[PDB]
Structures are given as C-alpha cells and as structure tokens.
Image 1 (cartoon, rainbow, N blue to C red):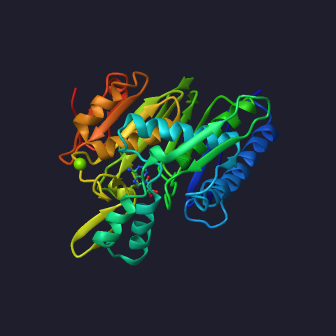
Image 2 (image 1 turned 60 degrees about the vertical axis):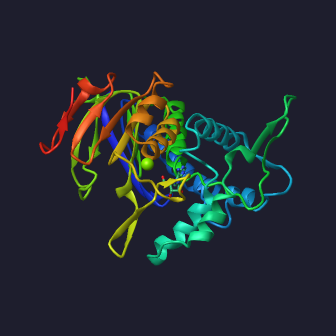
Length: 329
Ligand SMILES: Nc1ncnc2c1ncn2[C@@H]1O[C@H](CO)[C@@H](O)[C@H]1O
Ligand SMILES: [Mg+2]
C-alpha cells in the first residue's frame, strides 16, 4: 500500500476552504471522505451564517425576546462553548454582539462609520448573559436556546470556521484518516503528521501588513489548531481611518490594541478561534493573564514593531522566514 497525497478546495462559507490529506487507504475512501467534508461545509453554511435570512441562526435571532427555541445538539454545544469563552474573557469575546456587528457590516458595505447614538443603543442589546441554554436530562429531551433581551442577536462569525474545522477533523477521523491539513479561510487544523519519513506540519503565519501571499514565519505542529486574529483580515477605510472587523464590546468600535495579531494553538479550533478574538480585544498583558487559565493552549503574538513573542510550548517550533521579524526568546 502506497502513500498518496490529496487536496480539494472550494469556495464555501464565504471563503476558500481547502483540505489536504496523506493516506495509504484506497483512493476511493479518501475521495468519499472529501466529498463529505465539502457537503458538510455547504450544509453548515445554512445553519450558522449570521448574514443569511434562511439559516437556523437567523431563525433563532428572530425569536429574541420571546420563547425558547429548539436547536440540534451540535448548535447547542457550540453556543455553550461560546458562552464559556465569553464568561472567561469578561466578554472580550462576545457571541451576542450581532446588534453592533450588523451596524458595522452595513458600514463595511458602504464605507461609512455607524452613528454615535445608534451604536450606543445597539450595545444595550449585546448582553450574552441573557442567552439562556436549557436542556432536559431525560431521554430524548430537547435542547433549547432563549434570547431573553429584546433585539439581541447572536453572531458566531468569529468562531464558525473553528467549529467547522473541528467537525471536519472529526469527520476525517471517522473515515480512518489521521494525516491532514484543514484550512478554512485561514483557520487551520493540523491533524497528525505529514509525510516527507513523518514530519510535523509547518503552519504559516502572515505578516499582518503583508499581502498574505507568503508567511512571515512558520510553526511546526501536530494535532493542533492554529487560528489567528488580526485587523487585516477584514477592514474598510474612511477619511484616513481604518475600521477593522474585531469589535471591542466596551466601545462598540473596532478594538484599539497593542498587538497586530494573535495566533492561538489549541486542541480545538473552536477554542483557538474564541481565544484569538478575545486576546486581540484584550491586548497583550491581559491576554497573557487569560491564557494562564488554559495551560493546554499556546500563543504567538506579533507586535506592530515586528517583535514576536511565543509561549513555551511552541517557541522552539517557530522559524522566522521574513527577517524583518524578530522572535524574542
Ligand atoms: N469581540 C467580538 N467577539 C465575538 N465576535 C466578534 C467580535 N467582534 C466581531 N465579531 C464577529 O466575529 C467576526 C470576526 O472574526 C466579525 O465579522 C463578527 O461577525
Ligand atoms: Mg484596547
């Protein structure tokens, strides 16, 4: 039986999604797995999207201020995990920020900053503590979500790709695959080892102010997600000012922070995504404080002066490719 390398890529969930596999299984088995990966990505686009009218999430948001809504266990568990990171991060990551994000999403489309009072009003409808998850304990009992605050809206944009990367890894494993690189719009999961000999996957992290083509550094990892938050992934400009996609929930404006990017290395991409978002909002010192709560996670920060700091679990695995950057040790 020979090793073969495969990849497949499609535009889906608003972005380029690519999966690379090494396997000695029959090629028909790998093809079947990849078929299911990309079918899943189409199906979940219709469950999780905050910017479509027909999604399960859109339906949930339509019942804000009303009765509990039944959801499948997958969505329920994702919402539980999101609320866990909201609480741990003091709301720096907030999955109920839709009232504010939607004002900014139209701003992006129109290259215009939302209004002062409107934004102030929207912030009154973002209390994630008013998202009530309840699930009975008896056989077959439903899972429910209630949005208690009138006009509050869930937005899982910061974590949807991480969730889908974890679902993809679980699907690959279900198909007896153990070597893959999952890349959903830049949210990475490195499953197992690649082949050259078996070697770690070398995950690239971009120059925050670069074109994105080439990585500024790489980190060698196994069985790890790598998710990076940076202003650069999505912004608009108006009258000399850049407004990026990661909102500070205290201000209702794009976060003003002391790092250019934060990359989180975690066993679960869902977790890495939530934590990367929180850490970008919190800034470096408070991020270090939060991350001490999660010993199984590593982090790499790129500062505006091109210094790079990485935690102990990964620092020896970092290789700088763009010599303008310096890895502090
Ligand atoms: N502080 C935040 N916490 C959670 N999600 C956010 C936050 N700011 C923006 N978002 C959402 O996550 C996306 C950025 O990853 C945004 O497009 C928006 O949907
Ligand atoms: Mg700040």
